[PDB]
Amino acid sequence: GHMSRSEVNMGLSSAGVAVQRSASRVAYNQSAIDDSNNSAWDFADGVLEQILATSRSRGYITGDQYILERVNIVNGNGYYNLYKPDGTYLFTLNCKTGYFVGNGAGHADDLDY
Image 1: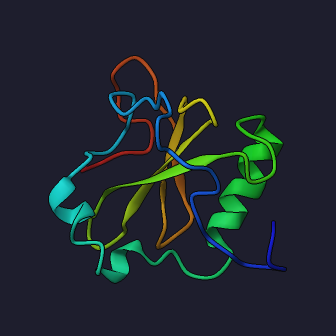
Image 2: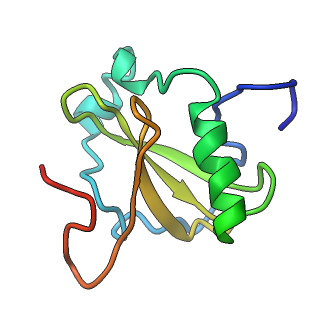
């Protein structure tokens, strides 16, 4: 919610933030993460802004006060975690589908991998 429509970004800086990474539903695979050149990391168009628009609606975040992070590549469905400005894990989303998965008592909510 800065440019106009369809942006896709991390919205806040996860630098110094106390972000919950161990709370992630998908593996933080730094090899796929560093493989960032993948289109597995290209969500689509305002797809993130969707999930984010949703996140705020859900009560996960506000505006672009979110902290998104690259996590994993499954099938090329590059998964991104959404965090609070405090780094609090909200969910793991699929960039390629704009789907998003929640977390619980150590179970696959939407997961399969």
